[PDB]
Amino acid sequence: ANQASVVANQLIPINTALALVMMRSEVVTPVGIPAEDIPRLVSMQVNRAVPLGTTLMPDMVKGYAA
Image 1 (cartoon, rainbow, N blue to C red):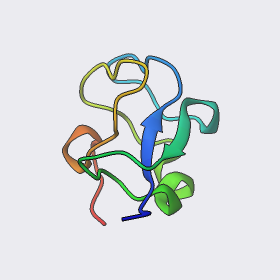
Image 2 (cartoon, one colour):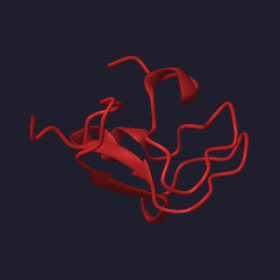
Image 3 (tube, one colour):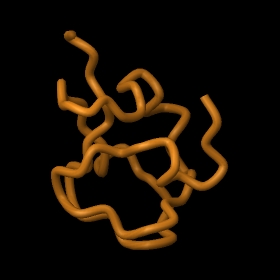
């Protein structure tokens, strides 16, 4: 219900390291990576370009295991 996910605050280019300015949280459906994992996501790379407003999913971040 009120579970917030990590949503792209800007387009994030392929193979680019995640920076805090790139990640906002939002209550979106389907649920993706929980918003409390934003600290852990810093400096991990995406394996695909992520458009603005996309929910960050576990399979999109290289090295991500919850």
